[PDB]
């Protein structure tokens, strides 16, 4: 009886616990990176472009005047 | 002409280059620092200086080079040591005297003051020539007679041919005139790292690479011009296989491209390769370095040089192939190249695609791997060369999910799949036969059939035996070896014998240091015949294990049988052992 | 023969950066001096230079700068450093100002920091051995001359105390096998209390002759924290190759150096690199580490032992992973051992050195060193497994050998792992202690130990 | 499940603890099976 | 602030609280000044919810007391950033310069954060967490700190801003900053809703920083704090016990383990659940909490001091 | 509640020498001090060596023993959660008893009561000394395990036979500091003497 | 489509389908005229495709559009376009039924991601461009049976 219970617990762990937690870790990593890092870098790039063309407009105005 | 205007770290913006081309190298400042042109905004350009940019003063002159990143090929390329940006390290150390690499060294890649015995071909002085013609041959060294050829993309009527004499690289030996103008050609020539060497026609790969190890030669053959990937990062097993390839492989010459690896590993390689020597069929001893061009790039070196080192090496290999010699190119760490790529991408601020890698990683990697194959040369006489890449994959964390690993696996044909577990299992070859795969097996049809008609069937049976073994391992772990059927028990025992003797080659012992194709094929034939004639016999398992133990000992003696005992002698011994096993198995049953 | 030009065209003060207007031909990293209107003198480094406009990052902050009343004198020298033999035995600030109440150093020669890289052909494989003093590193993951091994740790682990212990107990093994040794200790962004600890440790060291201590406080400017590794490695290179002395460099909490690099990169207004940290950190840390090696020409060598704090108590962080990729070793500080109060919290099982075989030999170290290293590692793993088994089964089902492994692990943790902070053990003494641990096993039980070597020492 | 690094660390710790517990339970099960086999031999 | 997600009846419980709002001191409490004068501000609410709230307040008989400010979803976004400020100003006047206790119901703070993000994007500033404006914390602080008692006047403002977790989370910037600012947090749990309990309040994460000062001899029984501490301890131990029983097996659980599971079941069944139009006194409610506590033995009630145990264990 | 990898947290733990990391679980457990005894750390330990020596030399070793007991309890909590308390030995039993005694008597300070409002160092050191002394005596008793008895039997015996000392170790918290240091020191010395009498008569009876 | 990860014989399956393709017949002039786009294939695979199609005798009715990985990455996007344009002309304005085959649909995607990253555009999931749904729609949503004509894609 004890060996059956222990074997059932071990098999259940191997087949369900890790097999569910590993996809959870993979999904967490994928979401975290591909959303937070990607969108933060995109926001920073958009801000850099905004500053760049603001400087370009300033230069154009200086050339005009 | 041209003065720096904005020097912001790696990038330097200089005015005056109205005519600068995209991706053209340019020299910056008094120190003659080297940089590439990226952005040609207006009359100004953009220079990413590879070396350190400190100390630069505004209006420092910038000198154009009229050439993209190019490697100076020709005679004398072999033997020497070169950096990622094609800088001869040994001559730099000799001339400079000091140990460090000076910021602004300008030593030419090949010393043009050295004299090479130039021997011209019988081509007529008033003849007509085109690109790729083997117009002469120069004895750059022993064992690697350099078959110099007329530069590609050049066709003309020859005007003058130099006689057989000692000449320098700067000395001119050729001149041609297709149009009214006549242009002289020297022995040294240049080619961009990016653009591949022109090839008349890619050819289907037909003949295999003989690594000298039984496992790779037999189980998972690799063709000439076939891409190979090694998952090696620790234990220097990849360096061991590289040394084996340098010593024994079919490659007429070998190029090792070490980029982005630790300095200590590079030093170990630079001392280990000269120690190694390659035995000729004549048997007299000749050093491998005379046939080997080594390119090393440490982490201290500039990142851009590390990225371009791969193309430098592959272009050298392409020159050797166009010279009509089979050549093997080994990349120490493709993952280090990927790290260099991510660093450059971050420097130039590209949009990341997957885990920080730039989007174009797949395209660059695919192009580099695809620059290797069996090739019909350009020009005449018609000869065929081959570049085969054994570039090594070094995944961080040992996960195939790494984008570089996935891309390589998508591109690579043969993946030998070295495993650290086998090294922990006291296996010297450490080649995981299971997780490794061969995709060139069908390509070896003609070669295997010519060498041995039953070799294909033997290989298929061996693969089936390996699969049955991996199943029977967990089957035995389930209940035990006894519960298995007699034929299943024989199969398990024969698979264990195969793994212990055939698959696992020590390569430390002189007898097993080099395993020829004939010896390996005969050992496989003996093993398969013993297994077969034992399986039909069943009689009992234990009973035949005892009565056929002499047959097992004779089969193991095939591993004892070595080319060191002589190839015909080894073949005769293997045939005798197979006959003895056949007689013992048949007569007993 | 060239005199500085004192510009007074300060136009625009933004954050930690000050911008000059009309500078005739500035150099890129020309170091620059700034006189405040009140007369205060503050130094700075010239950053990216455009056409006749140069932006400057200054030390000690930007407070007090006025557009009209601040003058900027251009030295035109790219951060040279005075270095000499007598630099030993003295403590220097982040930039290099002597804080030991001593005379400014008389320069043997002026050297450029971030020295040009070694020609890789000149590099040679690591050889010999060096006594860290701590037996666990000395045995399990040994370090040879020329090998760069980092030491991963986390906040709250006594990384700095262990570094000071190494500074005190460092010495060549060749003395036991039968004064060229030197240590350049650079501490980046250490706290005031740790600063006092290091200062007192140097005051009562008794080994000042062989130690130089670069010190950069938290209150010090971030750029000074950046340059401290550079000047440290420059002085080490001079003392090693130009002076023929084996040199052991310790860098503590290089996470502070990475943070300062992040700060300066943000100052450049460049886009942040992947995972927050700058992309160029790989190249920077490579330049920091790769200066360690063995030159074929010069007898002296350099050993690099960075003390890199691992954020979030893991190596998954970008900096620990990057430095592990670059370097060739990983010694670890286990949080549990500190929690269990073992002063050396070294995590022996995670500990590893790639070039352990090269360090151990017959001429240098004893022949049985590698054998006992492997045997102790395997036996410790077995002991941990048997401890788990005793936990799960109640310890009654265990055989005699299981109890042997349990008591071996207990004695190992009690004696070998725990070392006095001031207690010093020669590598021979460490091997003797490991052997005394080993005698409790039967002769046959030591499977890893080769024959004819077991009987050589197991006899006792 | 918040993609924040706290949840990632929690999940990693849970996976590591699960692996260690699985190894311990496997060892215990093997020992219990061996004892049961011996008892079965005696009963036979 | 009430913390809810999409679907959870935050609107219904808000309406319930508005009808049930009352004083408690010694169960004593016309009270026109004591009238709570509820100020209700709904931002970006579906028209169905708007009609729901309108009808709920109309039928409540407090139509002469309550005051509603509506900014529907179809209404322009910019209007929503002013509506809670208008509500706060009206509450401040009706409380401080008019001497009336005032209760404030702010609805869907996530919708307010959405308007803030829209404005920031339109003005193209540097983002904060998840692209939000970096000063969202300052805006929420200014929208929250405008409540509390004042020494110089008899009035007071108590606000109950219901908050919608976007992905049913707390690491989102809006709930995180709200927790940083607000001195409390009430959780509505999807797990409770799955079992169909009309008030889904998850008592475990719920907490009031000023609960200790709120409870007094006049306000409640002297053992109310002991009851709360015992309920926390029992619920936490019961959750740990339920996890242990799940991993080891139902049979393997100890006797005290089954006792803790029974306590959890009875608590989540009788205690948490309540009717929709039914209010309730405090003192007999504390008596029922003592019933749940005396389900556990006296020895297990280590958290409760022995004095209050003798005071109210038997009853 | 949030991650401790937050940039502000990471920056602080770089320079700060003492982190009194509170635990959300402890707060939910209504454990009022709520200080986690695993994440928290005080790097100032080496400096106070002279102070502790001049005050009470034995305090250092008993503090280390308490830390080791807490670490062992935290480590094997996972094991007992997985495997179960059945395999727990006598040493494990006394370790868990001492860990619970610490978690209840020592680390918990209500501070809303006169006896718990302020805990002077002299009372804290005596309580820790008593707990560690009881742990040591239990260890020695279960280690003796002779006379056809002992070990887990000895543990159960001292649990029942010496239950009065175990119960009043908890009440040692309730000892009012306002009564005066000499009186409290005398009471704690008497308790220590009685504890020494315990496990000595139990040693004499040999179970 | 055919879903198949790396290392699978899906290319051989596609070759078998193309060679064995035919109407149910439950004629030849209007029979299946197969168009075989090849977006980003290896040189060995390209040679395999050429040999299999030439030997099978299907060259009487099959057009190949080979694009190797060595080709410029942008030339990859226009391929599975040109292929569909030719298919439309052959089926609707010429009559014969067409069974278009695209290989490495993923390589087309990669080609888009690379081009989009070059253009510095707004990224969708995993760094792919946000409009890829549109740009696949423009490729997939062409096959069908226009009424006025007897062709079919």
Image: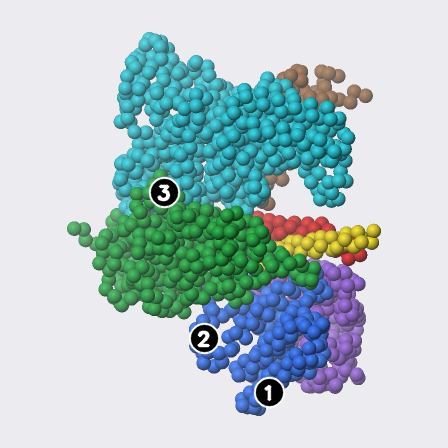
Chain colours: A red, B cyan, C green, D yellow, E purple, F blue, G brown
Q: Where does label 3 land, which residue?
A: C123
- Is residue G124 shown left or right of residue B78? right
- Does G85 sit above or below residue C105? above
Q: Is residue G44 visible?
A: no
Specify the farthest residue to the left: C1
Q: Same chain for marks 1 and 2?
A: yes
Residue shown at 69%/35% (left/top)?
B492
- Does E124 sit above or below residue B333? below
- Is residue G14 shown left or right of residue B382? right
Label 2 neighbour load within 10 Å: few <14, some 14-19, many 20+: few
Q: Position of residue F50 (x, y in %)?
A: 43, 77
**Which corner quadrant of the image does residue B303 belong to?**
top left
Q: Same chain for marks 3 and 1?
A: no
Task: Tell me which chain the residue with mark 2 is part of.
Answer: F
Q: Which of marks 1 and 2 is nearer the N terminus?
A: 2
Report the quarter where the N terminus of chain B lies: top left
Q: Where does label 2 land, which residue?
A: F48
- Check whether the beta carbons of the residues at disc 1 and disc 2 lie within 8 A of each other: no
**Which corner quadrant of the image does residue B128 belong to?**
top left
Task: Tell me which chain the residue with mark 1 is part of.
Answer: F
Q: Position of residue B471 (x, y in %)?
A: 70, 38
Label 1 neighbour load within 10 Å: few <14, some 14-19, many 20+: few
Q: Where does label 1 land, which residue?
A: F190
Residue shown at 30%/40% (left/top)?
B104
- Check whether the beta carbons of the residues at disc 3 and disc 2 lie within 8 A of each other: no
- Is residue B38 shown left or right of residue C245? right
Task: Tell me which chain the residue with mark 3 is part of.
Answer: C
Report the quarter where the C terminus of chain B lies: top right
């Amino acid at each position: 009886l004890t060996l059956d219970e222990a074997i059932k617990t071990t098999n259940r762990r191997v087949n369900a616990l890790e097999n569910v937690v590993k996809p959870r870790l993979e999904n967490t990593i994928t979401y975290i990176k591909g959303e937070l890092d990607e969108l933060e870098r995109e926001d920073f790039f958009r801000l850099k472009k905004i500053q760049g063309y603001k400087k370009r407009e300033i230069e154009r105005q200086l050339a005009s005047s | 002409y041209g003065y720096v205007r904005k020097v912001s770290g790696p990038v330097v913006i200089a005015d005056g280059m109205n005519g600068a081309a995209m991706y053209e190298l340019v020299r910056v400042g008094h120190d003659n620092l080297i940089g590439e042109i990226i952005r040609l905004e207006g009359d100004s350009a953009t220079i990413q200086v590879y070396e350190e940019t400190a100390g630069l003063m505004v209006n420092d002159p910038v000198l154009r080079t009229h050439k993209p990143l190019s490697v100076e090929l020709g005679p004398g390329i072999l033997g020497n040591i070169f950096d990622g940006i094609q800088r001869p390290l040994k001559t730099i150390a000799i001339r400079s005297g000091d140990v460090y690499i000076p910021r602004g060294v300008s030593v030419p890649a090949l010393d043009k003051d050295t004299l090479w015995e130039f021997q011209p071909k019988k081509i007529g002085e008033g003849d007509l020539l085109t690109g790729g013609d083997l117009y002469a041959t120069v004895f750059e060294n022993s064992l690697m007679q350099h078959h110099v050829a007329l530069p590609p993309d050049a066709m003309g009527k020859v005007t003058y041919v130099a006689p057989a004499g000692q000449y320098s690289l700067k000395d001119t030996v050729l001149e041609l005139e297709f149009q009214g103008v006549k242009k002289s050609f020297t022995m040294l020539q240049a080619w961009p790292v990016r653009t591949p060497r022109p090839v008349s026609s890619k050819l289907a790969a037909d003949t295999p690479l003989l690594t000298g190890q039984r496992v790779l030669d037999a189980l998972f053959p690799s063709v000439l011009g076939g891409t190979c990937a090694i998952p090696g990062a620790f234990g220097c097993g990849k360096t061991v296989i590289s040394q084996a390839l340098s010593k024994y492989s079919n490659s007429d010459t070998v190029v090792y491209v070490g980029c982005g690896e630790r300095g200590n590993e590079m030093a170990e390689v630079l001392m280990d390769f000269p120690q190694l020597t390659m035995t000729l069929p004549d048997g007299r001893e000749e050093s491998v370095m005379k046939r080997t061009t080594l390119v090393a790039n440490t982490s201290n070196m500039p990142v851009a040089a590390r990225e371009a080192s791969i193309y430098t090496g592959i272009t050298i290999a392409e020159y050797f192939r166009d010279m009509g010699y089979n050549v093997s190119m080994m990349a120490d760490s493709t993952s280090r190249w990927a790290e260099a790529l991510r660093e450059i991408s971050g420097r130039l601020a590209e949009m990341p695609a997957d885990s920080g890698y730039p989007a174009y990683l797949a395209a660059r990697l695919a192009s580099f791997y695809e620059r290797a194959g069996k090739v019909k040369c350009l020009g005449g006489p018609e000869r065929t060369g081959s570049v085969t890449i054994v570039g090594a994959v070094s995944p961080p964390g040992g996960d195939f999910s790494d984008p570089v690993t996935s891309a390589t696996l998508s591109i690579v044909q043969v993946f030998w799949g070295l495993d650290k577990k086998l090294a922990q299992r006291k296996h010297f070859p450490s080649v995981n036969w299971l997780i490794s795969y061969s995709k060139y097996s069908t390509a070896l049809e003609s070669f295997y059939e010519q060498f041995d008609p039953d070799f294909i069937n033997i290989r298929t049976k061996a693969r089936e035996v390996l699969q049955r073994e991996d199943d029977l391992n967990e089957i035995v772990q389930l209940v035990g070896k006894d519960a298995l059927a007699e034929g299943d028990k024989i199969t398990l025992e024969t698979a264990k014998l195969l793994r212990e003797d055939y698959l696992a080659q020590n390569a430390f012992t002189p007898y097993d240091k080099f395993c020829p194709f004939y010896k390996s094929v005969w050992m496989m034939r003996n093993i398969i015949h013993f297994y077969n004639l034992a399986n039909q016999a069943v009689i009992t398992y234990t009973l035949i294990k005892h009565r056929l133990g002499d047959l097992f000992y004779r089969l193991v003696s095939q591993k004892f049988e070595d080319p060191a005992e002589g190839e015909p002698a080894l073949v005769a011994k293997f045939k005798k052992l197979h006959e003895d096993l056949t007689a013992g198995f048949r007569a007993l049953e | 023969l060239e005199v500085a030009m004192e510009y007074r065209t300060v136009t625009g003060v933004a954050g930690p950066l000050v911008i000059l207007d009309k500078v005739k031909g500035p150099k890129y990293y020309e170091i620059v001096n700034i006189r405040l209107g009140d007369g205060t003198m503050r130094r700075g480094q010239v950053l990216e230079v455009d056409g006749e406009k140069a932006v400057v990052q200054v030390f000690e902050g930007t407070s007090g700068i006025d557009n009209k009343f601040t003058t900027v004198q251009f030295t035109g020298e790219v951060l040279k450093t005075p270095v000499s033999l007598d630099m030993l035995g003295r403590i220097f600030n982040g930039s290099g100002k002597p804080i030991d109440n001593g005379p400014p150093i008389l320069p043997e020669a002026y050297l450029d920091i971030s020295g040009s890289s070694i020609n890789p052909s000149e590099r040679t494989y690591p050889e010999e051995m060096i006594q860290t003093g701590i037996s666990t590193i000395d045995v399990m993951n040994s370090i040879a001359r020329g090998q760069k091994i980092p030491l991963f740790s986390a906040a709250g682990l006594p990384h700095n105390e262990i570094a000071a212990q190494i500074c005190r107990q460092a010495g060549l093994v060749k003395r036991l096998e039968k004064d060229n040794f030197a240590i350049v200790f650079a501490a980046m962004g250490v706290n005031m209390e740790t600063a006092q600890f290091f200062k007192r440790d140097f005051e009562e060291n008794g080994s000042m002759e062989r130690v130089t201590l670069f010190l950069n406080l938290a209150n010090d400017p971030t750029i000074e924290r950046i340059i401290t590794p550079r000047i440290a490695l420059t002085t080490a290179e001079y003392l090693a190759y130009e002076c023929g002395k084996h040199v052991l460099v310790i860098l503590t909490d290089m996470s502070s150096y990475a943070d300062a690099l992040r700060e300066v990169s943000a100052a450049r207004e460049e886009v942040p690199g992947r995972r927050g940290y700058p992309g160029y950190m790989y190249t920077d840390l490579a330049q920091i580490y790769e200066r360690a090696g063995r030159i074929e020409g010069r007898k002296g060598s350099i050993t690099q032992i960075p003390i890199l704090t691992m954020p979030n108590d893991d190596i998954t962080h970008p900096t620990p992973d990057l430095t592990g990729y670059i370097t060739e070793g990983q010694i670890y500080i286990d949080r549990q051992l500190q929690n269990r109060q073992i002063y050396p919290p070294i995590n022996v099982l995670p500990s590893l050195s790639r070039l352990m075989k090269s360090a151990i030999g017959e001429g240098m170290t004893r022949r049985d060193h590698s054998d006992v290293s492997n045997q102790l590692y395997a036996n410790y793993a077995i002991g941990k497994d048997v401890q788990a088994m005793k936990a799960v089964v109640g310890e009654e089902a265990l055989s005699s050998e299981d109890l042997l492994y349990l008591e071996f692990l207990d004695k190992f943790e009690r004696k070998f792992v725990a070392q006095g902070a001031y207690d010093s053990r020669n590598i021979f003494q460490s091997l003797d202690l490991a052997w005394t641990l080993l005698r409790i096993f039967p002769r046959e039980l030591l499977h890893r130990i080769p024959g004819k070597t077991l009987d050589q020492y197991y006899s006792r | 499940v918040v993609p924040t690094v706290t949840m990632l660390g929690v999940m990693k710790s849970r996976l590591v603890g699960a692996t260690r517990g699985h190894a311990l339970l496997k060892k215990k099960s093997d020992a219990l099976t061996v004892q049961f086999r011996q008892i079965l031999k005696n009963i036979v | 602030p009430l913390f809810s997600a999409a679907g959870l009846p935050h609107n219904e419980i808000a309406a319930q609280i508005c009808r049930q709002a009352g004083l408690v001191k010694r169960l004593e409490k016309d009270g026109e000044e004591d009238n709570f004068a509820i100020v209700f501000a709904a931002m970006g609410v579906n028209m169905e919810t708007a009609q729901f709230f309108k009808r709920d307040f109309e039928e409540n008989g407090s139509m002469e007391r309550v005051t509603l400010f509506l900014n529907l979803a179809n209404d322009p976004t910019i209007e929503r950033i002013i509506t809670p400020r208008i509500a706060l100003t009206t509450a401040e006047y009706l409380a401080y310069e008019c001497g009336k206790h005032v209760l404030v119901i702010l609805t869907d703070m996530s919708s307010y954060a959405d308007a803030l993000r829209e404005v920031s994007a339109a003005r193209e500033e540097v983002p904060g967490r998840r692209g939000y404006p970096g000063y969202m914390y300052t805006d929420l602080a200014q929208i929250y700190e405008r409540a509390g008692r004042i020494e110089g006047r008899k009035g007071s403002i108590t606000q109950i801003p219901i908050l919608t977790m976007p992905n049913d989370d707390i690491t989102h910037p809006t709930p995180d900053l709200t927790g940083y600012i607000t001195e409390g947090q009430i959780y509505i749990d999807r797990q409770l809703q799955n079992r169909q309990i009309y008030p889904p309040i998850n008592v475990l994460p719920s907490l009031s920083r000023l609960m200790k000062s709120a409870i007094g001899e006049g306000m409640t029984r002297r053992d109310h704090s002991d009851v709360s501490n015992q309920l926390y301890a029992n619920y936490a131990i019961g959750k740990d016990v339920q996890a242990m029983k799940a991993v080891v097996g139902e049979e393997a659980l100890s006797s005290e383990d089954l006792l803790y599971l029974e306590f959890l079941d009875k608590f989540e069944r009788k205690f948490v659940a309540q009717g929709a139009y039914d209010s309730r006194n405090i003192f007999q409610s504390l008596d029922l909490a003592w019933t749940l506590l005396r389900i556990f033995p006296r020895e297990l009630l280590h958290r409760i001091p022995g004095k209050t145990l003798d005071q109210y264990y038997s009853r | 509640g949030g991650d401790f990898s937050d940039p502000v947290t990471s920056a602080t733990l770089s320079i700060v020498q003492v982190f009194w990391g509170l635990d959300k679980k402890l707060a939910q457990r209504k454990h009022f001090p709520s200080v986690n005894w695993l994440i928290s750390y005080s790097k100032y330990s080496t400096a106070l060596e002279s102070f502790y020596e001049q005050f009470d030399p034995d305090f250092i070793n008993i503090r280390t023993k308490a830390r080791e007991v807490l670490q062992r309890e935290d480590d094997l909590n996972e094991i007992v959660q997985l495997v179960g308390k059945d395999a727990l030995a006598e040493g494990d039993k006394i370790t868990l008893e001492t860990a619970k005694l610490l978690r209840e008597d020592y680390l918990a300070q209500n501070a809303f009561t006169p006896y718990d409002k302020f805990c002077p160092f002299y009372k804290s050191v005596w309580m820790m000394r008593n707990i560690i002394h009881f742990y040591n005596l239990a260890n020695q008793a279960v280690e003796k395990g002779a006379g056809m008895d002992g070990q887990k039997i000895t543990y159960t015996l001292i649990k029942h036979r010496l239950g009065d000392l175990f119960y009043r170790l908890v009440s040692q918290k309730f000892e009012d500091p306002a009564e005066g240091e000499p009186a409290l020191v005398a009471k704690f010395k008497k308790l220590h003497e009685d504890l020494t009498a315990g496990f000595r008569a139990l040693e004499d009876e040999t179970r």
